Image (spheres, coloured by chain):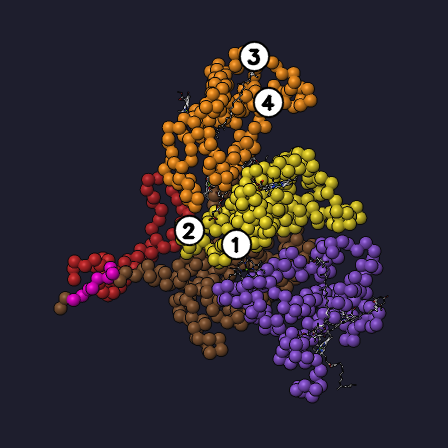
Chain colours: A red, B orange, C brown, D purple, E yellow
Amino acid sequence: TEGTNEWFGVDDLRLLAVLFLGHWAILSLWLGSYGDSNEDEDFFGEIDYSAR
Amino acid sequence: EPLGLYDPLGWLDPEKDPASKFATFHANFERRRAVERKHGRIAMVAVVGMLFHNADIEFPGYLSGELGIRFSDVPNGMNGLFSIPLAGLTQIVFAIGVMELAIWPASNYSGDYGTGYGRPFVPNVLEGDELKYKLDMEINQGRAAMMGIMGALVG
Amino acid sequence: GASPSADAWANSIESKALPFARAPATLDGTMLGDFGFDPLGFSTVPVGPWFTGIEGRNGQIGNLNWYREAELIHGRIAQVAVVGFIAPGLFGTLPGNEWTGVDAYSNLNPLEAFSQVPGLAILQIFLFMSYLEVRRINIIKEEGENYMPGDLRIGQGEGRWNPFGLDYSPEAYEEKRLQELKHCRLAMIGVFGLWAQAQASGVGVTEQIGAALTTPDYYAKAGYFLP
Amino acid sequence: SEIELGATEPLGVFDPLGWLETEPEAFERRRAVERKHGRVAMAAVVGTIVHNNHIVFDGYISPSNNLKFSDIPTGIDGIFSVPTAGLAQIIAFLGFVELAWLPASQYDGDYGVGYFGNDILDPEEKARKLNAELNNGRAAMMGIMGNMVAEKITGQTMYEQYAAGHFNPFNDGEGF
Amino acid sequence: ELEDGIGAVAPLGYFDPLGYIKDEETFIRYRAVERKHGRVAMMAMLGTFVHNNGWTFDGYLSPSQGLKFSDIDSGIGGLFQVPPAGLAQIILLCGFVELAWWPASNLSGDYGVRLGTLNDWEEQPAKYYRQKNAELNNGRAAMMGILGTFTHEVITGQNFAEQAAAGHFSPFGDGQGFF
Ligand code: CLA
Ligand code: CLA
Ligand code: CLA
Ligand SMILES: CCCCCCCCCCCCCCCC(=O)OC[C@H](CO[C@@H]1O[C@H](CS(=O)(=O)O)[C@@H](O)[C@H](O)[C@H]1O)OC(=O)CCCCCCCCCCCCCCC
Ligand SMILES: CC(=O)O[C@H]1CC(C)(C)C(=C=C/C(C)=C/C=C/C(C)=C/C=C/C=C(C)/C=C/C=C(\C)C(=O)C[C@@]23O[C@]2(C)C[C@@H](O)CC3(C)C)[C@](C)(O)C1
Ligand SMILES: CC(=O)O[C@H]1CC(C)(C)C(=C=C/C(C)=C/C=C/C(C)=C/C=C/C=C(C)/C=C/C=C(\C)C(=O)C[C@@]23O[C@]2(C)C[C@@H](O)CC3(C)C)[C@](C)(O)C1
Ligand SMILES: CC(=O)O[C@H]1CC(C)(C)C(=C=C\C(C)=C/C=C/C(C)=C/C=C/C=C(C)/C=C/C=C(/C)C(=O)C[C@@]23O[C@]2(C)C[C@@H](O)CC3(C)C)[C@](C)(O)C1
Ligand code: KC1
Ligand code: KC1
Ligand code: KC1
Ligand SMILES: CC1=C(C#C/C(C)=C/C=C/C(C)=C/C=C/C=C(C)/C=C/C=C(C)/C=C/[C@@]23O[C@]2(C)C[C@@H](O)CC3(C)C)C(C)(C)C[C@H](O)C1
């Protein structure tokens, strides 16, 4: 069924599971560099060169 | 300074030595100017009152939903305020009572409550001779409205 | 001549929660969780421990330990009452006898579940809430002026009850105090909304959210009839 | 002071367990408990006379429950026949009175109001009414306990029992 | 007065939390108003307790208008039920007290009303402070009660006898307001 109005084409909950697991996997890698990053460190430029 | 003796171009008769006879509080000039200005300001918004009601700007809607009184039901003559419910007329002069004591207190005999002239929410301050000139116009149009009401309420 | 609180609005330091409003001088910065939020000026008129008698009715100057005492267990009760407003609707209810009556513990509207469960259920909850408040007063009669607000002698430091070890570092402990206070202030707002929605809807919150996070029965597609 | 009041003529200072000589540190709280238990029982005894005389207000204490004031029993079961949301309103207000208005951690029992508002000027006219509060309070403790066990033993409330004439415990059907 | 600490009672102390007392002369003006408003609002709260309990006089308030005491509303509209010839009598007597007998110009609030042995202030000054604080405190609580009684009728349309018969004590789930 393709003309039915499903959120992101999710008609089975398998597809919802792989959307979460796919997006959380790169998030967890990305949190390996940008987790443990200080929230109160600001800057007054157009661009920040903070850390890695 | 709106309490000077130089506004209304002069002059009239009595000076009323009966006022200082045994009621000496009412013999003060500053209060008689505060009364004449206040009787003028009330009279001026009363002629526009008998211009708006008499042109049948009635209102959109009901005045009292439970008494079933719409705004087109109250008369246009001088029996307008004595035809609304007294539960409604009580709210009118209750709000005047907060005006008469708290917001624009009539014990302030100057009459200047810091409002300017033509601009609400930010006062239009008049500075020089035109400030001097608009004060007597307030009295002089206040006097024409005082005599205009008793010409429009005997008949 | 002047008020003792009119001079606290005369100094009137810069605020953080209301950064346009100039918080009064009685918020010194030295208290946990002070973000300069006192627009009505209650910290300028500090309260004392009135429950100890008439000699404790006065409040000392510049001491908000009893405002913080009332803040902490308004929020500690509120936190455990988010879950009380939610968990019967989520994790089911309890069964009843013929004595208590069947469906006594089963009212999923949490407000009339007060008026449905037996009185001995509420009386024993109230007496257990009473017992730890007897424990509170006995702590404030011993400690007196060296009484820390929110202390029921549960945890890390001196001769308190610690069945879990809980031996935090001395400044990870002040982060736990700030995590408690920020959850205290948040769940006070949260349990107000739960109490107000349970009146306004008539049902529990899982029963109002779950009905709004579901598709309507006239809108539900018939669905998946393709062989 | 307070240690000689509560001691009137027929018994003197009456302490058969001897806790005045043994534990004098606990006396002024124990006086405060005695005065509070007295004042609670005095309103409790007076309440049982008013209930059993069928002095009720009117109408419904709980119109949702369809429960009138006269539908309340006049015995032990009366405060427990009041609905759970109504009983919580009593205890919340009585906790407001016993912690804020008349804080019961104040152990001399003195809360700004005097005897009918007045301070007793004379120090032994004060001590006479301080003893009269304690003695009527101690007599009402036995009065409310003697009214509670004698309802649950005879099975009837105080109107029921007095209507029936069930006053003699020796010629009815009871134990002994 | 500030030095005795008349308004400052033991829960809150000197409760001037917004800083309105910036000297001693504006306290005497404000206390003259607070005590006057408290005396008016206390009789206003005893009115609504008596009116909403249905306790009325027997007979006609106005026999020439045929208006019984029983057919005056017990709510916020019951004063204006009364004919204006009749409550001009109320304004004229109360205005005569405000200018002659208990002149409200007196900022002290004393008008000599002493009910002797129930206030012997010269031999018990603690009873003076008890009755002076309780005139303010009962006046402050009745000032907020009459603001309660007024607005509960406005937002619900029912008076206090009618909204208590319906059990309408929650602004949630009803058809009134956006709540
Ligand atoms: C529970 C309420 C209560 C409390 C706290 C007290 C406390 C006191 N009484 Mg009072 N008294 C009471 C009720 C109470 N009394 C009653 C009901 C009567 C008989 C009507 C009396 C008759 C009485 C007299 C004549 C005198 C006192 C005195 C005293 C003081 C003696 C000091 C002491 O340690 O005594 C010992 C400790 C106690 C009395 C506390 C009671 C502790 C035990 C465990 C209670 C057990 C009672 C028992 C279970 C009751 C069963 C029967 C009941 C169910 C009907 C002390 C303040 C004396 C005084 O005033 O000193 C100047 C004194 O002369 N008492
Ligand atoms: C506060 C004061 C007070 C007062 C005025 C009363 C009054 C009464 N009680 Mg109550 N009662 C009280 C407190 C009080 N009580 C207390 C503190 C308790 C224990 C908590 C009780 C427990 C109780 C019970 C269980 C009963 C009463 C009963 C009564 C009624 C007495 C009838 C009778 O013959 O008693 C008998 C007389 C006495 C008990 C006093 C004598 C004491 C000696 C030791 C008894 C010896 C008896 C023995 C066989 C020797 C007899 C010899 C003799 C024939 C010459 C009477 C209305 C009876 C009733 O049905 O009415 C409600 C009843 O059954 N009372
Ligand atoms: C008639 C009105 C009125 C007036 C003139 C006063 C005046 C005073 N009060 Mg009192 N008070 C009142 C009503 C009033 N009070 C009420 C109803 C309560 C119960 C909430 C209290 C509770 C109270 C306590 C516990 C104490 C005082 C104290 C004082 C004194 C300190 C200065 C002050 O805070 O002024 C107040 C400021 C003004 C009157 C000017 C501001 C006017 C506002 C902006 C009007 C807007 C009000 C709004 C429409 C409705 C408010 C209610 C709303 C929150 C629901 C001063 C004499 C203290 C005292 O006596 O110490 C010795 C003190 O300890 N007041
Ligand atoms: C120095 C001199 C001092 C003199 C002092 C003398 C004072 C006299 C006492 C005055 C008491 C106060 C009266 C209040 C008015 C009132 O009661 O309304 C009477 C009616 C009663 O209606 C009613 O409604 C009822 C409908 S129902 O039955 O309940 O459904 C109905 O039964 C009833 O018939 C009908 O009347 O109530 C309402 O209309 C609600 C009004 C809401 C509030 C009005 C605000 C007033 C304006 C002031 C706003 C601030 C002003 C500042 C800004 C400029
Ligand atoms: C602000 C505040 O809070 O108050 C203020 C204001 C106020 C109120 C004006 C003031 C006062 C004065 C007060 C309160 C005066 C009240 C005193 C009070 C209430 C005194 C009860 C005595 C009862 C006794 C002795 C019982 C005997 C025992 C009896 C009667 C029995 O045998 C019970 C009975 O069932 C049995 C067991 C056996 C039967 O045979 C008989 C019956 C059936 C009856 C204050 C206190 O100064 C301050
Ligand atoms: C089941 C039901 O339905 O309920 C029933 C239950 C029940 C119990 C059966 C009922 C009953 C009957 C009852 C209880 C009857 C009790 C009646 C009662 C209580 C009768 C008091 C007399 C005292 C007198 C005459 C005093 C003379 C006093 C004199 C002459 C003095 O000089 C006194 C004195 O002090 C002074 C004045 C002056 C001083 O210088 C001298 C002294 C000190 C000496 C009811 C009514 O049927 C209802
Ligand atoms: C004869 C007959 O038929 O009668 C009928 C008809 C009739 C006449 C229509 C009726 C009526 C109504 C009547 C008679 C009277 C109502 C009277 C009145 C006078 C009602 C206002 C009080 C002031 C208020 C509420 C607020 C002050 C509020 C404030 C905020 C302040 O004062 C501000 C201020 O303090 C500060 C905060 C800061 C400083 O900068 C100083 C100032 C001072 C500025 C009746 C009697 O009902 C029935
Ligand atoms: C604070 C907010 C506020 C509310 C919520 C409110 C409510 C009612 N007003 Mg009021 N009112 C003001 C404020 C408020 N009024 C103000 C600032 C003024 C200008 C001074 C004012 C003037 C009048 C007049 C002349 C009348 C009047 C009425 C009603 C009545 C509808 C009756 C009905 O639904 O049948 C309801 C309850 C009529 C009336 O009372 O008739 C018995 C009537 O004639 N109002
Ligand atoms: C703050 C103002 C206030 C309101 C607006 C209010 C309202 C209701 N009271 Mg409450 N009340 C007090 C204050 C207030 N009550 C106070 C100061 C006390 C003395 C401690 C008190 C005592 C009791 C008792 C014993 C009962 C009781 C009840 C109800 C119920 C009736 C409608 C119904 O129940 O259908 C309505 C909602 C009964 C009840 O809760 O029944 C489940 C009941 O048994 N009340
Ligand atoms: C000095 C002696 C005295 C006389 C002889 C007298 C006479 C009448 N009064 Mg009374 N009066 C007072 C004193 C006197 N009144 C006092 C001290 C107060 C408290 C301030 C007061 C209050 C009210 C109110 C609220 C009403 C009222 C009325 C009438 C009316 C009845 C017949 C009628 O219906 O005309 C007749 C003329 C009603 C009314 O005027 O209705 C239009 C009405 O509603 N009065
Ligand atoms: C100088 C002196 C003279 C003097 C003088 C003179 C003229 C003095 C002045 C007297 C002046 C003071 C007279 C104004 C009254 C107007 C006031 C403001 C009231 C208005 C009334 C308003 C409220 C009107 C309201 C209505 O219309 C409205 C809005 C709607 C209608 O539904 C009903 C009502 C009624 C509610 C002598 C002594 C005579 C002799 C000699 O020559 C010298």
Q: Answer whether labels 3 and 4 touch (C-beta < 8 Å).
A: no
Q: Give the Cα separation between the discs numbered 4 and 2.
A: 49 Å
Q: CA distance from mark 3 to mark 4?
A: 17 Å
Q: Are marks 4 and 2 on the same chain?
A: no
Magenta residue span: C218-225
Q: Main secondary structure of the magenta part?
A: loop
Residue underneath mark 1: E161
Q: Separation of disc 1 and disc 4 at Cα?
A: 48 Å
Q: What percent of the width, then of the height, locates residue C187?
A: 46, 57
Q: Amino acid at mark 2?
A: Gln
Residue A19 in the image, given as x and y percentages of width and height: 25, 60
* Label 2 SS: loop
User: Looking at mark 4, is its residue's CB closer than 8 Å to ligand 11?
Assistant: no
- Picture layout, residue E76 above or below residue D17: above
CB contact under 8 Å: marks 1 and 3: no
Where residue B97 appears, as percent x and y from the top left, is 54, 34
Task: Tell which quarter ligand 9 is in.
Answer: bottom right
Q: Amino acid at mark 3?
A: Leu
Ranked by sequence position, the earlier of labels 2 and 1 is 1
Q: Which residue is mark 2?
A: E176
